Amino acid sequence: QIKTLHLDIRAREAINTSAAGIPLSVVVRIYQLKDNRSFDSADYQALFTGDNEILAGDIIAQKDVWLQPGGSVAVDMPLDDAAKFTGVAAMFLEPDQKKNTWRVVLGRDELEPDTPRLIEVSGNTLTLLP
Amino acid sequence: QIKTLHLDIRAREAINTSAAGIPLSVVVRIYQLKDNRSFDSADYQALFTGDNEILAGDIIAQKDVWLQPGGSVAVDMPLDDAAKFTGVAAMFLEPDQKKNTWRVVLGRDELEPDTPRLIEVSGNTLTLLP
Amino acid sequence: QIKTLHLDIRAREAINTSAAGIPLSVVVRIYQLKDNRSFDSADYQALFTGDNEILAGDIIAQKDVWLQPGGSVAVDMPLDDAAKFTGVAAMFLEPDQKKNTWRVVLGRDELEPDTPRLIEVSGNTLTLLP
Amino acid sequence: QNNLSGVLHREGSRWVPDTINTRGLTFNPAFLKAINTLSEIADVAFTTGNAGLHFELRPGTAAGVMQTTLITDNQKLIYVNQMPVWKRFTWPADTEAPGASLSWVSTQAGTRQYADLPGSWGLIRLLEMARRKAAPGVASGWSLSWQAQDGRMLNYTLRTEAGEGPLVLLKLRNFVLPETVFE
Amino acid sequence: WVSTQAGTRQYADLPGSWGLIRLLEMARRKAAPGVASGWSLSWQAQDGRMLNYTLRTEAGEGPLVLLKLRNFVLPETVFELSGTSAFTGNDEDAGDTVEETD
């Protein structure tokens, strides 16, 4: 299947803008899951600050990338074989927990073994690209 | 060619300063033109307040972005195929109509399909960046 | 069947008149539905402001046209194949929710592949034309 | 309550000086006029001991005007000539950058600014430019108005609770407290 | 709570040491014919899902008595000449009457 996890994270200038419209940085976390159901059940608060060890136990490993406004950070991760779902979540100033534009789940099939998949951050949303 | 219009609009703190030097906000409009000749013929007044329907008829669609002093707003626009020229115009307190630093025209070729082009506003002028 | 969605939206001068008889503009939305039953169940309020995601999930895509009083806007839409029903709804000042003259449903069969179907707005009602 | 009691005596909202002990004592009528303004402010603005009030509003419709202006302290109200509803505001909102502005898109114009202000009170400055008059609201109707540079004036109705809301805060603009209470 | 067709969504989080008396205000449909101090809570959250509880306190009324402090100012004068003949010895029963029925 896929041996090495490759991700490329783009970012425009207007990301995580405050009430003054100020371009702010953001912290994005990468999760290697055995279960995706608990990753779809947690809210914004119990995922980044909570002690849901049912979700944390399904997290095999976690790695935090840290991108400037208007830049990019490449992800070269030795992908675990039990990592059925690559959990991508971000911490905006205004995370829309309702419309759920702050997290995406990338399964085993949608990875590429020698090409990074492109995740673009804009405004306060997460966006994939073909 | 180019399918989706992507623009990134930067702004410093000293934009649209009054006679008291006060940092003021500004309104920028995006135009999708079929003709660029009428976009180079209108002045500051007949473009923002006028009824030049020869120019407005060449405008396929218009969209108004609205940026804070010292911030940014990302533009994700479904780009029309007849939009040969992306018209960018701003409304400063002191628009220099003579030296014409208040409008730029971005053609079909200078767009990027998956990367926003950078437009920086400073003082009362509009500036592109490579 | 039909590949490209073509619509032509006419408008007289007396549309969306207030209590002072003043000609006002209006916003019309185009919906691409998989189900027409939920489009016939929602009222004026839960369609334009509500979070009926059962109806919104049946909406494949939405596009908002925006017409002047006494004018027209052409609709050139790449028609989805699962879009069995073209939902047309408007937001008048006085939407008659009872007699239901504020929405029409255009199915797969009544479209034309290279000719726009004519939707005429008058008063506060929506009217088709042969 | 610590140096002029016995002659000044609180009765509801005002404290009209009424006893036989005021004889040989003539109050400056500037004083009694000023301190009845500065006690009728304290039944609208600062009723909870600190700053803050609450008031709701509703826009209207006009010729060529089809839009929405008020964004005051990061609670926007958007109208494209749909049905009118009442939205709840708060004047001293919790933000790091307070302010207000307007926005109007004509049939001849796109979005044009009308007001721009970096103040802690931002809602009250563009009420000074407004022209307020009576309205048949629910208890105290208030139809407002604003004039653009190209005509096409707007309409905005206003609901408030027990007082009349933040329109009383325009009374401060000529205010100088007097200096002598006695003759 | 966790709905049948959605994940967790918190009702309301209230910070500060005086928070427990703040969020407990909103469901005073309380009187219960069960245990001795016999109280229940409704907590009608969004979309019709209700979540019940049945409170049992220890000494008198427990922490529900802290709701009596709302809209409570220490009054004016003692020993006033005004109010010579007035019989208002029912509000201490009537406030709990409206409380323990609504």
Image (spheres, coloured by chain):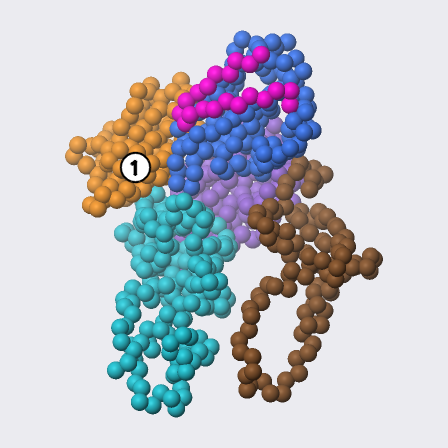
Chain colours: A blue, B orange, C purple, D cyan, E brown
Secondary structure character of the magenta stretch overall = strand
Residue C86 visible, this orientation: no
Against E14, is D168 above or below?
A: below
In this view, which residue lies farthest toward the right?
Answer: E34
The residue sitting at 31% across, 82% down in the picture is D27
Magenta stretch, residue numbers = A59-78
In the picture of the structure, the residue carrying the numbered disc 1 is B13
Given residues E20 and B42, the one toward you in this image is E20
Given residues B70 and D180, the one toward you in this image is D180
In this view, which residue lies farthest toward the left?
Answer: B98
Q: Quadrant of the N terminus of chain E?
A: top right
Q: Position of residue B55 (x, y in %)?
A: 29, 35
Against E85, is A115 above or below?
A: above
Q: Position of residue B26 (x, y in %)?
A: 31, 40
Chain of the residue under label 1: B
Q: Position of residue C41 (x, y in %)?
A: 65, 45
Against B37, is E89 above or below?
A: below
Against D28, is D75 above or below?
A: above
Classify residue D37 as left or right of residue C39. left
The residue sitting at 45% across, 68% down in the picture is D43
Classify residue B126 as left or right of residue E20. left
Q: Position of residue D1 (x, y in %)?
A: 42, 75
